[PDB]
Image (cartoon, rainbow, N blue to C red):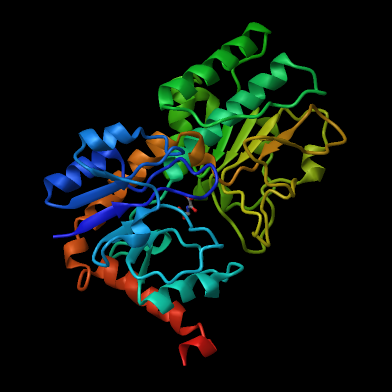
Length: 371
Ligand SMILES: O=C(O)CNC(=O)C(=O)O
């Protein structure tokens, strides 16, 4: 039987959690023992975990926990922490894609004889990820897209969409979006048309769900996926839509989805592009109309068009953080079957694959300290 210890997040403003009070309750029902660190920045109240049966402990207590506990967290630890990592850790560590400082991250595990099971690389036997955040990335992206479009109906071009902040629950977000939307319609604006590229995936499903909940008619949504995009861009449907939401990550040389030439047109209706797949490291952006990665404090950036109405991009790479509760609940539910295999981790392929991947990347690290 396994003991899990939920590490309080230390990444600034990280409000999500790898285990929710609901998943904790379910794991305890399956015979797990669960510690949960008190965390002020978590969107979950510590008392939810207490009612779920967790043992409540101070933030950072994982550092002195018995070596047999599996330390689970969502995001990175402070790069300023240097002490050896002696536990088995489950987390996103962001150190398998040659990220700055990746060798140092792994060296902490190496020195401590610890283990990293990286959440980004946990996959089923078919090679599909067991847990990610696509649905709420799309849902939050669509929400902000509608808000920006509504803002443009109700404000002058010299004003930009103000700072946004995480919401406590989905209902609260839908209410805000719907209020903005209804105020836009009051002006004489028509219900927006929305083009979604990647409509069939989790991101697309999430975007569609938000739109429906806000009251955007299904007839106003153009649902594109590979069938359509494989024709090759640029696509006229992009400037003709009121709002364009991209869910497909593309990083190879290919004809762009749109470009400044196609956007520089007085007949363009497009007001808002939400690139849910925004990645500042992407060498080949298929929507090459922005270079800034926007953020909650400054969520939109101007596309510098020479004709047509004001156009902005939302290029936030952490959209799920707009709805940290639901994002966590979905992620943790998706992860739960794998977590149930932890007693069997020495043999269960989902965990063995992740261990061997860790081993392989550690072997890439050559250091005099290891001699
Ligand atoms: O889900 C992924 O592939 C990577 N996710 C994150 O870095 C995150 O959600 O904070």
